[PDB]
Amino acid sequence: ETVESCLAKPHTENSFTNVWKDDKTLDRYANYEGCLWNATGVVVCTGDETQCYGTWVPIGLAIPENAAAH
Image (cartoon, rainbow, N blue to C red; front, side):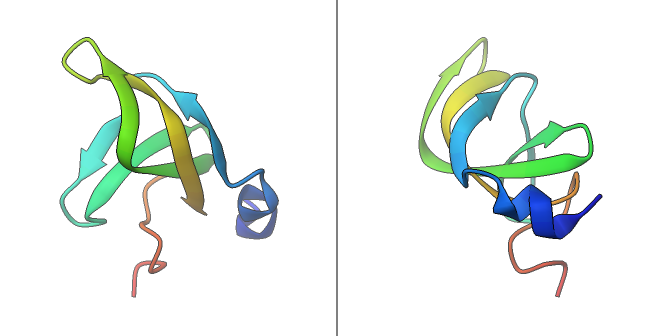
């Protein structure tokens, strides 16, 4: 994936369902097939928080945190 475009995205303003949370990445993240957003705190969650919306800053193609796996 083009991490440049995945980041050129609107930056968070969006959402995703079936969201997950990596203890490695250390944060909330939504696998947008090819893209990976990241939720912080204020994130509307429903269904045990499996689906949510709010700000999902873009950072990985589909799993890496914001530090870029450093």
